[PDB]
Image: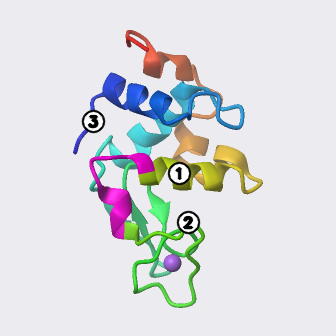
């Protein structure tokens, strides 16, 4: 599913991302825009052989199991494919674990390069929240 900007904001807010570990909702929306273009089905292969899954491009080397990333972990205890659903629950739950891991939202390269330090509140302007 390809979310609209405010639909996803609302969905994120209902699943408790809003100010999670001190990151305001706009950060999360901005990160999803640049990582996946709001598409729960996006996948991207990495040079190391791992794959990034879903709206928040969560990586198979540490967080979910794809059966094809040797020696990898599965800290979120979920098959990666589950992160691709129309229901973002599982992605949000795994994202909470990532952002708590010590580097905050910097674990998302595109947040760091395209959202950090910008007026992230723009991403929720106009939305009935
Ligand atoms: Na894995």
Q: Nearer the viewer, residue 54 or 44?
A: 54
Residue corresponding to mark 1: 93
From this viewpoint, is residue 56 visible?
A: no
Q: Residues within 10 Å of mark 3 (few under 14, many from 20)?
A: some
Q: Is mark 1 within 8 Å of ligand 1?
A: no
Q: Position of residue 88 (x, y in %)?
A: 38, 46
From this viewpoint, is residue 16 visible?
A: yes
Tell whether 8 sits left or right of 122: left
Residue corresponding to mark 3: 3
Is label 2 in contact with label 1 (beta carbons under 8 Å)? yes
Q: Position of residue 40 (x, y in %)?
A: 30, 50
Q: Earlier in the sequence, mark 2 or mark 3?
A: 3
Q: Residue at x 38, y 13 (%)?
A: 127
Asked which quadrant contains residue 123, the reply is: top left
**Residue 80 sits above or below residue 83 on the image:** below
Q: CA distance from mark 2 to mark 1?
A: 8 Å
Q: CA distance from mark 2 to mark 3?
A: 23 Å
Q: Earlier in the sequence, mark 1 or mark 3?
A: 3
Tell me the SS state at disc 3.
loop
Q: Which mark is residue 85?
A: none
Residue corresponding to mark 2: 76
Q: Residues within 10 Å of mark 2 (few under 14, many from 20)?
A: many
Is label 2 in contact with label 3 (beta carbons under 8 Å)? no
Q: CA distance from mark 1 to mark 3?
A: 18 Å
Q: Position of residue 38 (x, y in %)?
A: 32, 41
**Residue 112 sits above or below residue 49 on the image:** above
């Amino acid at each position: 599913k390809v979310f609209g900007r405010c639909e996803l904001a609302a969905a994120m807010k209902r699943h408790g991302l809003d100010n999670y570990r001190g990151y305001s909702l706009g950060n999360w929306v901005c990160a999803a825009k640049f990582e996946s273009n709001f598409n729960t089905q996006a996948t991207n292969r990495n040079t190391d052989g791992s794959t990034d899954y879903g709206i928040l491009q969560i990586n198979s080397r540490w967080w979910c199991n794809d059966g094809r990333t040797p020696g990898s972990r599965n800290l979120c205890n979920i098959p990666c494919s589950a992160l691709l659903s129309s229901d973002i629950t599982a992605s949000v739950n795994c994202a909470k674990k990532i952002v708590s891991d010590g580097n905050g939202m910097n674990a998302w390269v595109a947040w760091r390069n395209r959202c950090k330090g910008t007026d992230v509140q723009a991403w929720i302007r106009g939305c009935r929240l």
